[PDB]
View 1 (cartoon, rainbow, N blue to C red):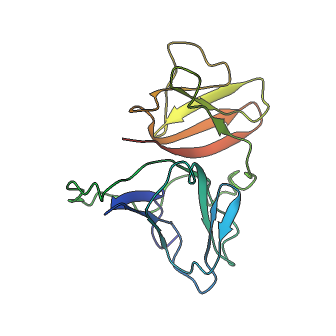
View 2 (cartoon, one colour):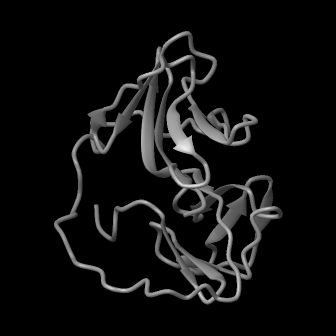
Length: 186
């Protein structure tokens, strides 16, 4: 109802990575990284000083005691010598409460079923979804987006080097996943 309701926001600052969680910084807020979890993180924005894709290639999450519902985001990037360019400016658009949510909409069951590809030999990224479903569909910003190479449980994102970058939601036969934040090297 109240507070922000946007997706995770990533921003690299001086070889550091600053992520923004959609949950106020409570005195019990925690973060997670793929398999390991970062405790004592009572901050809304998680910082990653000296980012390393090799040691930091997976997903991320944020949740609080009162908030047992969190979304799994994909964090994968690289930094070096504070590749500080000019990441500034940030307009303000309309974004206060969305539709379909207060009607007991399905959006809880989501541990780690979705997967994505990146190193397929050529360097192509294939986002997989459906969750063991024989049927899978992907949507972008609330609009369906089909591929030009079929949807064999995967999604055509492009050359990991510079292609995958954005949120993508999927819908399986009886299992629909939330907008996956695929943040790859830019």
